[PDB]
Image (tube, helix red, strand yellow):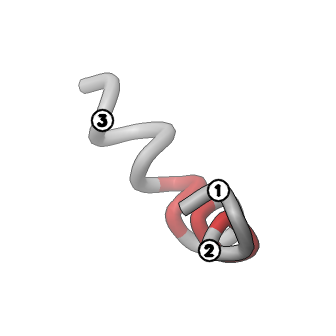
């Protein structure tokens, strides 16, 4: 999400999408 789903996409999912996505 980039509209307003980004609010948690990079607050909770920050340690997921920025982690397990790369590795």
* Residue drawn at the location 65% of the way across and 56% of the way down: 2
Q: Nearer the viewer, mark 2 or mark 3?
A: 2
Q: Which mark is residue 2?
A: 1
Expressed as whole percent of the image width and height from the top left, the position of residue 11 reads: 70, 68
* Residue drawn at the location 52% of the way across and 54% of the way down: 15
Instruction: Determine crowd level at label 2: few under 14, some 14-19, many 20+ residues with C-alpha closer than 10 A.
Output: few
11 to 19, vertically: above or below: below
Q: Which mark is residue 21?
A: 3
Res. 8 image quadrant:
bottom right
* Residue drawn at the location 29% of the way across and 41% of the way down: 20
Q: CA distance from mark 3 to mark 1?
A: 17 Å
Q: Is residue 19 left or right of residue 11?
A: left
Q: Is residue 9 left or right of residue 19?
A: right
The quadrant of the picture occupied by the N terminus is: bottom right
Expressed as whole percent of the image width and height from the top left, the position of residue 5 reads: 62, 74
Q: CA distance from mark 2 to mark 3?
A: 18 Å
Secondary structure at numbered mark 1: loop
Query: 3 and 9: which one is in front?
Result: 3
State the residue lying farthest toward the top. Answer: 22
Expressed as whole percent of the image width and height from the top left, the position of residue 23 reads: 25, 25
Secondary structure at numbered mark 3: loop
Q: CA distance from mark 1 to mark 2?
A: 6 Å
Residue highlighted by disc 2 = 5
Mark 3 or mark 1: whose residue is earlier in sequence: 1
Res. 4 image quadrant:
bottom right
């Amino acid at each position: 999400g980039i509209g307003k789903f980004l609010h948690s996409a990079k607050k909770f999912g920050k340690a997921f999408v920025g982690e397990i996505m790369n590795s």
